[PDB]
Length: 56
Length: 218
Ligand SMILES: *[C@@H]1O[C@H](CO[C@@H]2O[C@@H](C)[C@@H](O)[C@@H](O)[C@@H]2O)[C@@H](O[C@@H]2O[C@H](CO)[C@@H](O[C@@H]3O[C@H](CO[C@H]4O[C@H](CO)[C@@H](O)[C@H](O)[C@@H]4O[C@@H]4O[C@@H](CO)[C@@H](O[C@H]5O[C@H](CO)[C@@H](O)[C@@H](O)[C@H]5O)[C@@H](O)[C@H]4NC(C)=O)[C@@H](O)[C@H](O[C@H]4O[C@H](CO)[C@@H](O)[C@H](O)[C@@H]4O)[C@@H]3O)[C@H](O)[C@H]2NC(C)=O)[C@H](O)[C@H]1NC(C)=O
Ligand SMILES: *[C@@H]1O[C@H](CO[C@@H]2O[C@@H](C)[C@@H](O)[C@@H](O)[C@@H]2O)[C@@H](O[C@@H]2O[C@H](CO)[C@@H](O[C@@H]3O[C@H](CO[C@H]4O[C@H](CO)[C@@H](O)[C@H](O)[C@@H]4O[C@@H]4O[C@H](CO)[C@@H](O[C@@H]5O[C@H](CO)[C@H](O)[C@H](O)[C@H]5O)[C@H](O)[C@H]4NC(C)=O)[C@@H](O)[C@H](O[C@H]4O[C@H](CO)[C@@H](O)[C@H](O)[C@@H]4O)[C@@H]3O)[C@H](O)[C@H]2NC(C)=O)[C@H](O)[C@H]1NC(C)=O
Image (cartoon, rainbow over all chains, first blue to last red; front, side, top):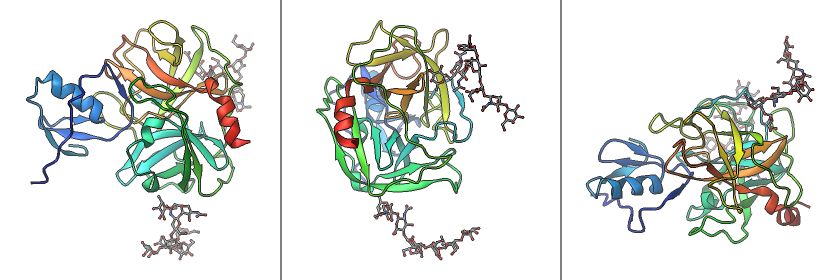
């Protein structure tokens, strides 16, 4: 109901920047930032979704 | 930092933590009493007014009497390019000026366009991830790296830990790379994820920006 989203459309990217702004995936993994999360969503071939912002 | 080790308390007393309300998000280096340097991409698309700048830290999880906490008054950029990850440096002016003591000191920077060559021995450090889902460090970690020229472009300083899956990870952006005492990079990006053992980590090359740094800090 929080309708949490990130836009992963410009993905994949060969490189990520190193800031920590964690994202908690539907696989119950913490991704380090949007870039690391989005590269995983394209590599899940779209079945990995966003649970919420922050750590798991 | 993946594969490194605990720093000694206040070993690198120019190491700064940048924090938003959830805590640490990037590193920074103290380069004058009222100025810190970081990566441009840490402040892009965040509310700079919310960022607290912590000096004097060692273990982020603990209440430390050592710490000094500022807010950011102004930022200076120099054509950061998010597409190509170029000029990934920022300088933040603090709303005050630090007290210099054993826990907080200003770093030394190289002269303009001094180049490191292939094989130089340096230290990296940071409070980022200890590994793909081992989580963020409490205690400042350091890591011996080597400068590398292969698989790097000329507008970056690159490092690699030979024979180990180690290097910089999320939360170590903006942290220094120190080589013969002087500050040569600002951690900028990875590729293939952290500690791939294949692609070197990329820093922003401070020596390219010293004239610009000087034009701020005197
Ligand atoms: C540059 O910007 C800096 C950072 O700014 C922040 O971040 C940015 C991003 C933005 O969000 C800003 O809006 C934000 O503020 C900024 O630093 C800020 O500045 C604020 C304003 O100056 C400041 O806030 C207030 O400070 C008051 C200080 O009073 C306390 O300390 C003194 C000195 O100790 C005491 O005399 C007081 O009694 C009081 O608390 C008690 O202090 C002592 C006892 O006296 C302490 O005891 C302990 O210490 C002993 C030392 O010997 C030792 O023996 C120990 O064992 C132990 O005894 C405690 O008892 C303590 N009690 C506590 C801590 O509860 C506060 O009074 C005031 O707080 C009150 O009101 C708030 C609002 O209602 C409440 O939240 C709060 O709970 C209290 O009720 C308030 O905090 C910030 O502290 C500071 N922020 C930082 C560092 O993050 C700079 O000012 C600015 N610089 C510039 C512009 O030049
Ligand atoms: C991984 O990287 C680290 C760090 O890398 C360097 O630093 C960073 C910041 C960047 O600049 C990098 O580019 C640099 O590479 C590497 O660590 C470095 O290792 C070098 C040796 O391997 C070393 O050089 C040699 O130093 C010796 C003298 O050291 C003394 O004094 C200096 C100045 O203070 C100090 O830096 C040293 O740590 C050491 O200090 C003394 O230490 C002892 C033990 O802790 C203290 O004694 C204890 O103290 C406590 C205090 O409460 C208590 O009293 C105890 O009771 C007591 O026992 C003592 O107090 C300290 N003294 C002082 C004054 O503080 C030299 O003898 C040596 O000489 C010669 O040999 C070299 C090799 O041939 C030559 O190059 C050289 O020219 C000489 O001929 C060296 O020069 C660095 O000091 C060290 N740097 C740091 C920052 O720690 C590491 O090598 C690298 N590892 C890998 C595997 O790659």
